[PDB]
Length: 63
Length: 77
Image (cartoon, rainbow over all chains, first blue to last red; front, top):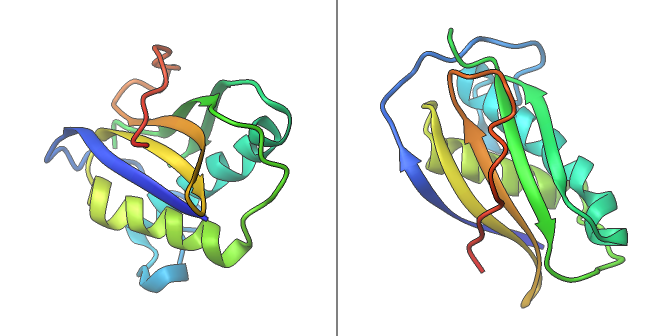
């Protein structure tokens, strides 16, 4: 399984709130990057029901 | 900071009854966060794949607005 991605819009805006449980997997040092990874992970897990049974939607996660 | 939420706007490409292991989901997640977003606000277009099969399309949005950006999913098949 893999995620093929491209940045549609890239910025240098670092104004992102901190979070609880910043990810430490895949060599992440927690922090803001870990907050983003934990957010992506939750969204991917949520979408499993939609590839299993079809459908779309908008899913969110605190970052 | 200003951004407090990340959003995923998705649509199904193909039905796939399989499920990626935690190890795979973590690798997907870390790659995008570290090499795509790079700790900054932005928009990513993506496709979840199961081997060579294109399964799901997701537009990932990280912006100042905490509100649902809506719009359409975008992909990277």
